[PDB]
Structure formats: C-alpha cells, structure tokens
Image 1 (cartoon, rainbow, N blue to C red):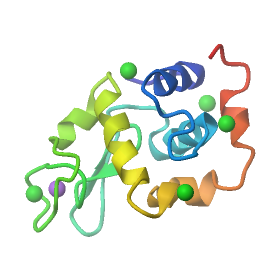
Image 2: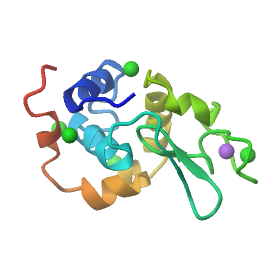
Image 3: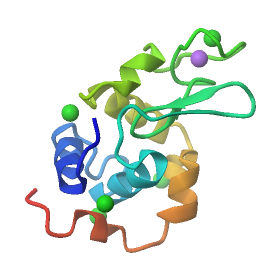
Image 4: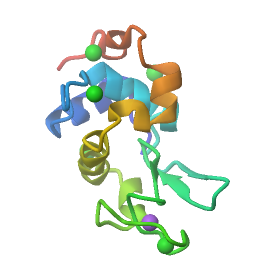
Length: 129
Ligand SMILES: [Cl-]
Ligand SMILES: [Cl-]
Ligand SMILES: [Cl-]
Ligand SMILES: [Cl-]
Ligand SMILES: [Cl-]
Ligand code: NA
C-alpha cells in the first residue's frame, strides 16, 4: 500500500507513535517519506546482505527474520514480511522497540540526514488529526 501523507499521519497516531519516545508525529511521517516514499511494500538490500523492509525500512540484521541474513537477530520477533503489510501495526510496534534502543531516531539514516533538525511539523500540516 502507498499511503498518502495525512493518511499515514493518522494511522501512525492511531497506533501510538505520536510523541513516542518524545518524537512528534511529523518526525515519523518524515522518516517514512524518505525511507519508503510511504510504500509499505518497499524492500532494499544492504551491502552486508541484510535487507530493509516496509514503510520504515526496518533491517533484518537485528529486528526481523528473513531467513537469509546470517548471524542476525530477530528482536521484534516477526518475519520481515510482516513489515510489508498494508496494516502498519507490525512496523509501528517494531519501530517503537528500535527507537527505545538507545540512539533514538538516529537508527534511521534517512531521518538523521533528511529530517533531524528540519521543520518536521510541515509533514502533518493541514491534516485532520
Ligand atoms: Cl508527500
Ligand atoms: Cl510534528
Ligand atoms: Cl537469517
Ligand atoms: Cl494501518
Ligand atoms: Cl531521543
Ligand atoms: Na534477522
């Protein structure tokens, strides 16, 4: 599923991401924009052989099982395919674990390089929330 901007903001809020770990909703929407262009089915292979999955590009090296990332962990206790569903619950719940892990939203490279410090409230502007 390819979400619209305000549609994703609403779903993230319903799933408890707004202000989670202190990160306002616009941070999460901006991260999803630059990680996946709001496409739940996005996948991208990393040089190390791991793969990123879903709207927040969560990596099989630590967070989910894809069966093809040797030596990796599965800390969200999910198949990586769960991160591709049109329902964002699994991606949100796993993101909550990631952002609690120590480095906050810096875990998302696109967030650090493209969202951090910017006017992230623009990503929720106009949305009925
Ligand atoms: Cl947009
Ligand atoms: Cl915001
Ligand atoms: Cl594996
Ligand atoms: Cl959803
Ligand atoms: Cl933080
Ligand atoms: Na894994």
